[PDB]
Length: 261
Image 1 (spheres, one colour):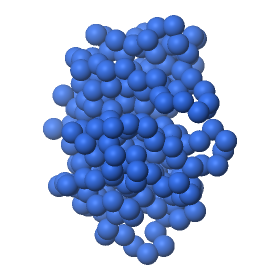
Image 2: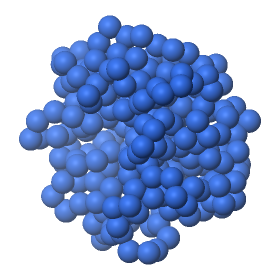
Image 3: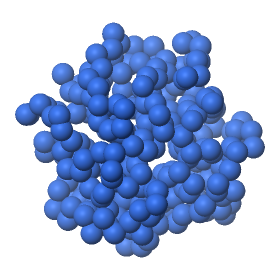
Image 4: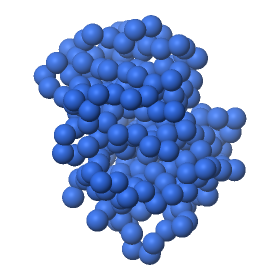
C-alpha cells in the first residue's frame, strides 16, 4: 500500500516485513520480518532511491537503471524488473498496492505516462496532466497533479473537489488521506476514530486505518475502523494491511511496529 518512501512494509499470509534505505547514505536496503522470500531475497549490493511493499513482495526504484525491482514471492505479480518492460525505460516513482505495482514513466519530477503490473491492472496509462506522488490502494492507484496540486485516482473511487490542494497523499486499502497544501498542513481522508485537527508532517494508510506524525511533537497518531505509542518521536512512518512501523534513528536495530486491525 501507499507511496514510494525511504521505508516500506510487506504483508499477507507470507508474513510481515519492514524494509528501509540504510542511514549511511549507501542507498542499500535492509529488511526485517517473517516473510523469508523477502528477507533472504533482499539485494545486498543493489542501490535504491525509494521502496514500496505489497502482499508477498517488496519493490524499489533502482538508483542506476531507474527501473522497478521487486523481491519476495507473489502469485499475482512477477519479481525482479516487471515484464512487459521497454528496454532502457526509466521511472521517477513506484507505488505497490496489495497485488499490483505502478511506475511513473520518465519522459523531471512529473509525467503523464503511468505503467502498472499485476492482477487485473497490467495497463499502459497516458493521462492529460503532469502527475507525481504516486500512492497505491488495494484496487486503485492515486497521484497529485503537478499543475494544480489536485488528487487524481484510477484503476467505485470516491470523488474530492479539484479545489482541494495537497502537498502529500497516502492511499490505504479503501481510502486516501491527504495533507492539505499550506502552513496549516491539516489531513483530509475520504473513500469507501475521526482524523486529527493538528498539523501533520507525514501520513500513511493501512487497510481500514491511517496514521500520521504531528508536526509539533513528532508523536504518532492513528485513526479509522481498526492505537499508537504516545511518548515516542518518529521522523517517518510506514503502513502494511493491519500494522504500522515508525523509525526514530538509523542505528542498527529492528523496527518499532504495532498492530491495529
